[PDB]
Structure formats: C-alpha cells, structure tokens
Amino acid sequence: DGIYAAFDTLMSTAGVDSQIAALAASEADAGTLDAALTQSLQEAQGRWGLGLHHLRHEARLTDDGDIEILTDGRPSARVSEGFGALAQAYAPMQALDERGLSQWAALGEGYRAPGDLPLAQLKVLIEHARDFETDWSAGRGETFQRVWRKGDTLFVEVARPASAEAALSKAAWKVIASLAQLPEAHFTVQAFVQTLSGAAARNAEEYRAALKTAAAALEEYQGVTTRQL
Amino acid sequence: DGIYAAFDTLMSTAGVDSQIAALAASEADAGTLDAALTQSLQEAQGRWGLGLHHLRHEARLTDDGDIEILTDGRPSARVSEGFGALAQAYAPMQALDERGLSQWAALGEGYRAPGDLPLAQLKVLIEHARDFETDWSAGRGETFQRVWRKGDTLFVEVARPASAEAALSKAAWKVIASIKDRAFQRELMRRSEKDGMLGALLGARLAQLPEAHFTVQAFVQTLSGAAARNAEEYRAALKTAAAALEEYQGVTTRQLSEVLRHGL
C-alpha cells in the first residue's frame, strides 16, 4: 500500500494521474496493475525530459510487494529504494547538451534530418517516408521541438527545459509567502509528446495541429505540477 | 564435370563470372569457397528479376559434396538437382504482376511511396528519410524502375522483364545467321517460317539448358555512404543500371547462342 502510493506520487510529478493505489484497492488483477504501472511510467517518460525514448520503459509488481522499474528489460531501480535511487539509475543513460536537451535519437543510431527543414520537405517525409527522425529546433516561447515516426505512429515533442531545483525554489518561497525523499527534487515536467496514428501519422496538417496541441499541453502540465508543489 | 562447374554454369545465366571451379582448385584458404558461393549467388539474384530482395540468400557445401541453395536459412534446392529444380523451388516464393515485375516490397510489409513521385519530392526522401521504398514506375527504353534504401545502401533497380523463351528465341536468330553452310541455313530459315525459329533450331538436336529457367531481367545498382543520399547520384545510378542491364543481356544472349551452336 505504501509502494503503490509512492508510485502514484512519482507519476504526479509528470502530471500523470495513475491511480494505482485505488486500482489496487479495487482488487484489480496483478496483470491489470502491471499494465497500469507501465502505461503511466511511459506517459511520465514522455514528459520528464530525460531523453530515453530509445529504451523500453516497464514497471512491474514483485512478490515481496515492491514495484520494480526496468529499462530494456534490465532491472534499474525499485520504488521502495526511494526517488533518489531511480534518479541515480537513470542518469548514466542520459546525455544532455548545454540547453539541457537529449542528444540521443529516439530512433537509435541512424541519420537525423535538420531540425529546421522547410515545411515542404517535412511534408514529403510525413507523407511518403517510412521511418525518419529530425533533431531539435528553436521554437516559440523558449521551447524546442522535433518530430519522428516509428511504425504507424508519428511523434511530436515540444520541450522547455527547466531543472527540478528551480521549480522547488519557486513553490518554496511561494508557500513561505503563504526534501531528498521528494520526487520533485529529481523529476519535473520539461516536455510533452503528442502521438498521431494511422492516416493521421501521414497527414501534414495533422502534424502542425499536433504541434500546437503538444505546446499547449506542455504549458498546462508544467503549471499543474507547480500548483501541486 | 563436378558440382563447382555446375554452380559456375548456373551463375553464367546472370552473367556472373563466379570463378568457383578455379577457386576450388586454387591455393586459397578453407571457407573462402562457401563465402564465394553466397557472394556469387546474391549478385545473380539481383539480375534474375525473381523479386526476392526481402529474403536472405546463401549457398554452402554440404556433407556429401553438393552445393545447397538456402533461402532464409532453409534448404531450398541442391545444385545437383539441375537448374529447373531451382526454378520451381523459387516459384512458390514469387509473385509477379501482368508485366513481369515483383509485387513484393524489397523492404517487407510497410508503406511504399508512389513510383511516379516528382523528382523534387523523391530527392527529399533521398536526402533525409531513413529507410524507404518506391513502387515500380516506367522508365526510358521500355524499362521499369524502383528504388529503396536499406541501411546505408541505396538500391536502384532497372528491369526489362522477359520470358526465358523469348531470350532463347533471340539467341536462335543470332545463331541462324552466323551459320556457315548456306544450304542448311536456308533449310533452317524455311522450317523457321513453318515450325517457329527456336523450334526449328532445337529440332536439329531445353530443360537441361540453364538459360531455359533463368534469365537477366533486371539489374540493381547500389550506392553507399555519401552518394546514397545524393539525388543526382540517384539519377546517374539509373542510367548506369540501364546500361548494365543491356550489357549483361547482351553477354547472356551471346553465351546462350554459343551453347546452341553445339549439337548442330
């Protein structure tokens, strides 16, 4: 019960409302819970901005009542170990630049197109290419963006890097106007990823919409976690 | 004359000089031969126009001195069964449209870009997409053409589908012309007016004929590294492979001819 609750907390930093403790309280089957814990972890991975879209992210129930968080099937950390432990197990996988963006390609080693292509070269990729990835590009509001397709799914990302420490500082002096075991000290909402499927993942107007959508998402979620905090 | 010459004869049908019989006899190192069979076999597949780019091809030596032809790691045929045997092992695997073109994608199931794309749009694909594939379009010289990229290698296919029958027909004409004994030439030329040409020339003496089951129908140029992302390297690639396909068609027609002159 501690363990599901703690997980619920971890996801709360990404504005993900996993409801795992409740769903457990409902006597849901172990498979249903696993599925729920994995869906959430992937949803949070999208928004956390750590840059691990190239690894598989899973979370699963263990016999001793723990949750085990894996990456590419390799047991990375446990929740009963604390939010710090998870932070310290993710770190050697990332690779940030000087603005704080991931340097990995979400599609893995391979060719990466300019972030800045004309929207008509982008439209050709979108309509007639199988897989493809672009790199970051400077967008509005100090955010950055990029797009890739993997399978039947087009992935739009909008990312405005911000460290966890600063958000904590803001909400701290905002509460005084009114920490190592807090996940908000390692995890915050930096990015948002919108997905398109089937016909939509080959439609250029649809990609443009999905940009405006992911951009409005990132700003809402960035704010929600600050108001929780 | 041995299983290596049998494999060498089968490779001449795509105009591949494998040199397998000479390697087997050379002072080379153990294992270099299997590698050679597979190298020669894959090149041959590029030219046969069978449409099997999605399968993996291998040839090895077996425990009883035979050469085994593999598809996706599974035993498909044995060289000693003759070349017809190889033809029908490939058949259930193929899928030809009305024109003689493979209906399979070279990249397996997935999206195929149009084959009639505008050059400005095909370029974007060539400079920035990862793996991609186009459909068959027509090209110049009553040819067809498609292009894919798998990895770091661009694959430019030019094809002019033909039945091995017509190829045998075209080689018969070339021979009944070069004939020295003008009397027998006019005899053949008259039977050819009646019973057909390749008909009347065979009639002076085929399923054992390797070219009866395999023919040069296509060619695949390949680009690597920087050229593979270059749209003008692509347009040149297309002219090279059409010239290649004419060449190897010419080589294999002159070969089948010199084969038809034996037994006259």
Image (cartoon, coloured by chain):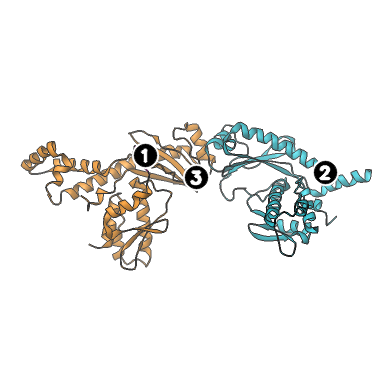
Chain colours: A cyan, B orange
Residue A93 appears in the picture as rendered: no
Question: x, y (%) of residue A138?
Answer: 69, 38
Mark drawn on residue A93: none
**B94 to the left or right of B200:** right
At mark 1, the secondary structure is: loop
Q: Nearer the viewer, residue B10 or B122?
A: B10
At mark 2, the secondary structure is: helix
Residue B161, relative to residue B17: is it above or below?
above
Where on the picture, by quarter, is residue B10?
bottom left
Tell me the residue that label 3 is attached to. B226
Residue at mark 2 to residue at mark 3: CA–CA distance: 48 Å
Where on the picture, by quarter, is residue A116?
top right
Residue A211, relative to residue B61: is it above or below?
above
- Circle 1: residue type: Asp
Residue at mark 2 to residue at mark 1: CA–CA distance: 61 Å
Residue at mark 1 to residue at mark 3: CA–CA distance: 34 Å
Q: Is residue A83 located in the magenta-colored stretch of the structure?
A: no
Tell me the residue that label 2 is attached to. A226
- Circle 3: residue type: Ala
Tell us which disc is closer to us: 1 or 3: 1
Residues flagged by tags 2 and 3 on a common chain? no
Q: Nearer the viewer, residue B150 or B64?
A: B64
Question: x, y (%) of residue B143?
Answer: 34, 36
Tell me the residue that label 1 is attached to. B97
Q: Residues within 10 Å of mark 2 (few under 14, many from 20)?
A: some
Main SS class of the magenta portion in the image: loop
**Chain where mark 2 sits:** A
**Chain where mark 1 sits:** B
Please report the bounds of the magenta region as a residue range.
B95-100
Residues flagged by tags 2 and 1 on a common chain? no
